[PDB]
Length: 45
Length: 50
Image (cartoon, rainbow over all chains, first blue to last red; front, side, top):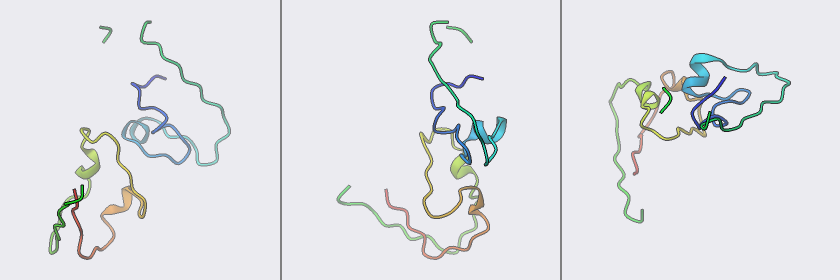
């Protein structure tokens, strides 16, 4: 899934955030590796 | 900054939910209490420095 910029501030174990708390939270005991990279080049609503 | 104002607020019952529902706020931080558990607690001499 994709977010507009302010991602890491919300995506984290036990991390609040309006999008994070309304769409999808991670488990408190979580074991994974999230990656992020810009895809603006890929005006487009 | 050197001349901040201290507004003391008491005897008030306000919805402590829109204080984070404001999307205009760039980033919301809490250091002493859980942000979701703001309504339950009882306060004393709230300050409003800016």
